[PDB]
Length: 49
RNA sequence: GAGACUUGGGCAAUGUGACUGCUGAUCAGCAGUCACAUUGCCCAAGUCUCUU
RNA sequence: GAGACUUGGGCAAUGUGACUGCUGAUCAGCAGUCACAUUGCCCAAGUCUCUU
Image 1 (cartoon, rainbow, N blue to C red):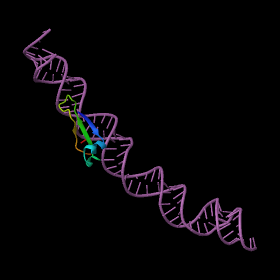
Image 2 (image 1 turned 180 degrees about the horizontal axis):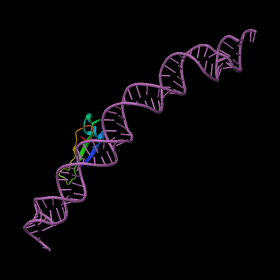
Image 3 (image 1 turned 180 degrees about the vertical axis):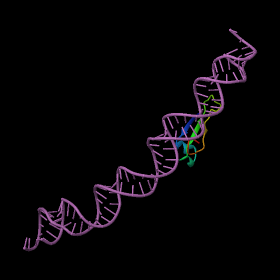
Image 4 (image 1 turned 45 degrees about the vertical axis):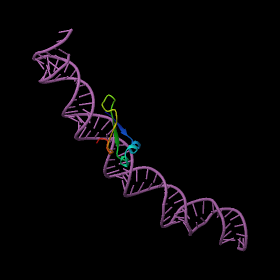
């Protein structure tokens, strides 16, 4: 899986004010994989969790 | 070689636990220096007025 | 000399400004290093099947 970290502007562009200090990441699949769409994460602080 | 099992070897992926340094951001607490401002003590110094 | 006026300078208490350094906390992040797990691939032979 290809994970793309979402910077601050896209965070509150797609999510609420909670995405200010709490990071958001994305999940991206190849077309060969069943999913051809992206998956987004819960706005939350540390990337590890 | 393949199908499967037995053991071993090779590679890879991903995750987990621990350690040593390295910086980042924010916040509190402390010291020192320099400068400006207020008025006064204030003498120097020139000008000017009075006058010495 | 008195006074006006100005430059020269320290001193006086007091005010504010700018800079560096010092200890202390939290969070995040980096580069290393060891230890364990699963998954997948490959190969070897043990066993047999299939095929050259």
